[PDB]
Length: 199
Length: 238
Image (cartoon, rainbow over all chains, first blue to last red):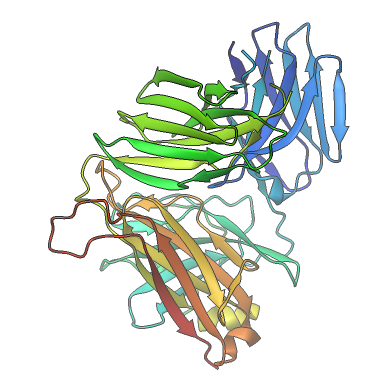
């Protein structure tokens, strides 16, 4: 038995729909569960389907099974960023689970009022050292990790100020060098044109 | 439901390691081991029902001996680890649904010589950002640590906060070329500018590092890079 999981990485905008597609080889297989793994955490059960049934729905989740074609799929309506995780499909007849390689699902949040900006931040004791912070940018902006191995750049990351109901993207950069300041930091990344660069 | 100890472990080449999994509810007597490799692929190892059952099995690259000692305890010995991995204990009733425990993470090092704890620094909100957005972002930088076993958290006036926080999901390598490169991780806490501007408000990022124990030998002049917390702080300014 091998279980194939077709999509490896899956990036989708908040609110839109997603699918993951799996196939299995061993016709004895009759139980097909799905598990998710939020980064740096354990595996949590999501939903399952058995051999009697073709379609099962639970809240925003739907699973399909076609036994004849030996394929099955997870459908997520109205993705939220909380859905971001690695999803795994599995199959079971030896009553063990055979697992697919996983699909990384990223749900990028919809930034209501973009305000792209690159700010400089000082050490609380002291000063320089300092760090450059790219923030408030739109989800469709992509941050690239620089072509100079002596300057460090984080990937984008989403935070949620739960009240007042506000989400924001952020990336951090820093070096130890002469020739590095915030004006030049995210050169190498597209970056909007209206990015605020203060003094 | 299911406890596994330890939750983490350092393993130099040569050392074996023992893992325990205690079942906390007798309705799910069927207990199993699954490995999850560094590429995230899960693979079943064993399922042991009765006390006294033991089995052996070899995968690339780790060798496993598993033993169901009691009706509620399952043990696993892991030896000859080339590549690191994570080990999940599962339990089940009639084998159908499988509940996965919290897992034990194993990292493998050639040398103990290259373990280091993190240095931690907090960077205070830009004034520009406070004027422009009426919001304040603290950044926390944990640098120079190895292996990548840190848990970063933010503490505001002595209580832990989750709102406003985002930590990098992946640490980045300081010298990406090297095989045993020390790591670095950033995190951000974002608050209202009014809250940052109260100087009675105290901020700390805390980095739990996981490193050597009493049982690990240590030969070098610098301090033994033991399991420890490293913190950094900042105060509100008006």
